Length: 122
Length: 233
Image 1: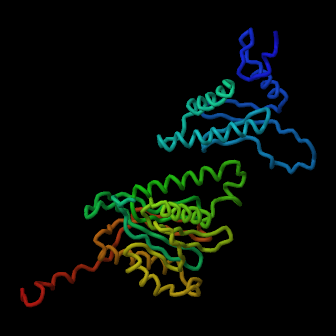
Image 2 (image 1 turned 60 degrees about the vertical axis):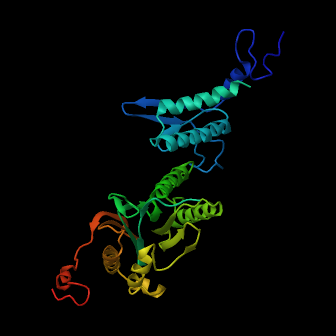
Image 3 (image 1 turned 135 degrees about the vertical axis):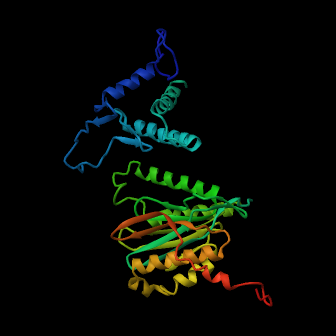
C-alpha cells in the first residue's frame, strides 16, 4: 500500500524517510550559497535574489555567525535555517561555559547534526 | 547566602572634561593573606567602557564571562555591531545593575561593588556604580571600599560638582587618581602596590595602562619615631 509519506518518522518499504526527502526539495527550490575551504580558513557566499528595487540594498543579510569564529550559510526555508543557528549559538555557549575554549568545528557540526537528525525521529 | 572568599579591594574613578579614568590594584586577598598578585580587576568592554569590580573574585570572574557573552551575542545578526549598535556603557551598566538586584532579591548575591566607566556614542562621560544589593548611583567621582573613604575626599577636591568637570584635564585627573592610589597603599592593609589604570577619552578613545606602581613614597620620616610616648631612644 501507500501513505508512507504522510508522517515524518515512517520508514518506507525501501527504507527511506520520505518527509526528509520532500524537505530536500524545499531546499533545491532555493537560492545558492557555497563554501570554499582554503589554506587557513573558509569562505562563504550566497546568492541573494533581488525580488524588487523596493528592497533596501545590502540589508537583508543572510550569512550568520555562530559565536565569533563560525560562519553559517544555508539555502532553503530561511526560517528553518535561522532556527538551526539559534540552537547552534546555544550549543556553542553551553560548550564554552563548561570548557572555556570556543567550540571546535567538528564538535560544532556534530551538535548540529544531532539536532537535525533528531527531527527525523518523531 | 554566601560569604566572600578571595577578594579585591577599592576601585576608584572620576570623570573629567572629555572622558573618565578608573583604577584598581592587582591583588586578590584571602582574608589577611595577600594571596594573588596578578589580578586584573579592570574589565574593558569594547572600545568605550571599562568596568571595575571589587568584592569576591570568583563572582568577578563570573561577571567577566557574562560580559564577554554580552559582547558575543550583540554581534549576532547585528550588521552594526562594530558601530551604531555597539555596546554603550549605559547598556552594560543597566544590564549589570539588573543582575545584581535580581541576585540580591533571590538572596544569592554577587558579592561585588562595581563601577562602570565609559563614554557614550554622543560623547558624554558615563560613570556609575551598582553593588551586591542593587543600589546604584552616579557622581563626578566614585570609589568602592576604602576608596570611598579616602579617595573620594581627595578626588572631590578637584571635581566638587558637575561644573568642574569641563575645567579638569586628563593630566590633572590622572595625577589625582595616582595619588589616591598611593594613599590607599599607605592606609589600606589590603592594598597592593601594583595597579591598573584606564582612561576613556572622547578623542583618544580607550587607553588602558597595565603594571603601574605607587612611587614618590614618603617613609623617611619613620626614623625619628621611637617608643609610644615617654621613650627617649
